[PDB]
Length: 191
Length: 191
Length: 190
Ligand SMILES: Nc1ncnc2c1ncn2[C@@H]1O[C@H](COP(=O)(O)O)[C@@H](O)[C@H]1O
Ligand SMILES: Nc1ncnc2c1ncn2[C@@H]1O[C@H](COP(=O)(O)O)[C@@H](O)[C@H]1O
Image (cartoon, rainbow over all chains, first blue to last red; front, top):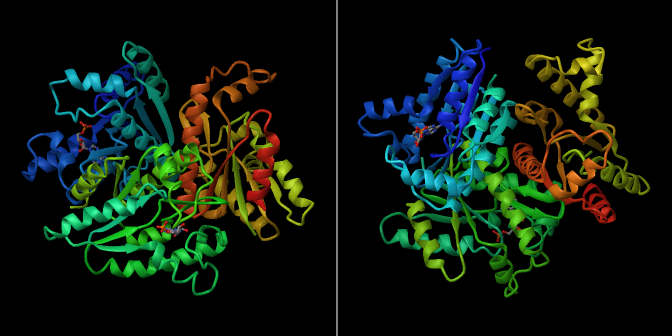
């Protein structure tokens, strides 16, 4: 079976860019990853259905709809994993008006059957401040505490995925002024 | 077909009080939840078999007895899950002398198959303080920290239930002097 | 017969604390067969000629390790028929690739545990204990990383109970307070 890696982090923690940088590094040494964005895969389906204009509105849809578009996005990537080792960029849980939506519910977890789950964190202070200057996307500008709460539930969910699939769960800190350290750590676990 | 909701909280956090007020609010606008107490559907049995006379000692009768009066208790509520909007007042985990007992183990969970799991919290100081002025119930011997620990594990359990069922997990603070704030939030998520 | 999982990070003394407690129960009529899950894995893997030395236990590929885990679980479930069993193991093992579940769902289904015990203490005391130990003086862990491991161990433990219905008991085993931990363990295992 092809390696399936799940990378997660709350919006603004920089899990996407730091993992991308790590995978650019591993490319230069023979390691290849099919970087997939779970969010983009379901965004294309949600936009195609005229439900959303931008990716940041999907978590505002009612759970029933989010889970349906989630189920679909799952099959897409599961089929995508059949050709090469996949690095799925996504979320341990999504913060919706109805609460934390598990990003990899029972059935999706089984489709993807990941070997590794990476959780990229940092402090809520840094995450708020980063979201504060980011004009590229629509963030929820919560409090450092709310962001910590989200990271708390992400750990819980991530560890559940690990217990169900046997996947290992890696927690990596991506702190301000320390991206290099984060990239090195991510590169080693993904190698 | 009917929206099933699980409302949880440690004793004294007032999860029942607050969510009920929210459901009263939603009645005046159409939404009419049927408030059912798992703690009642699961008490009619213990009181019958003379296992438990007082509701506040079911979590101590026997780990191999309360887990048995739980399974059937859920099978009965699994029925109303085929009626109309149902709100199940129960516990994420019950603090028994043998440890934290999951309130929605795999079996019971599949019956209810909830859409939303609500976790009502507040600081250990406030919960401990509320308990100390309550006599119609007895469960005081804990500390602000043991209460936090229980809430810690309740978050974990709740999220695992979410992962297994696809349900969203909503955490609501019900802080002293701010019941109106909690009620507003509960009203919005329950809609 | 009760199947019990005893966990704790290295250095917390979960194994020794549990043993003292099980001895105390022995002198009371309750007899627990204490086994290490890792040892059981090696035994069954050696019995079916998958391995010869415990050194090769690391070289096992994902498929064979899963098989060995099921075999260990089936074996322990076999022991359960004869007496209460205490499986000494790790909720998660802190590896370079992250936290590895000690008891994946496929093992949980075989074990059907009734109680998961989680023994803890502060990161400071755990690091202190490890430093005054001849073997571990070059692991680079801090009180914080140990707290993080204990955090993930709690989530894994709670997930174990959610999937099996077992109760999860957290027990503090603090410096100078061993007797108290032993009494608690003695009471939860009784
Ligand atoms: N596993 C998932 N389950 C449900 N929704 C997801 C999942 N992964 C990503 N998303 C959604 O995609 C949106 C944008 O993705 P992202 O660019 O990674 O923030 C998120 O806000 C979520 O609504
Ligand atoms: N889902 C559940 N699983 C096991 N016990 C429960 C559950 N829900 C309620 N109870 C029991 O009912 C007792 C009283 O219910 P409550 O009035 O809601 O605090 C608790 O102490 C528990 O023993």
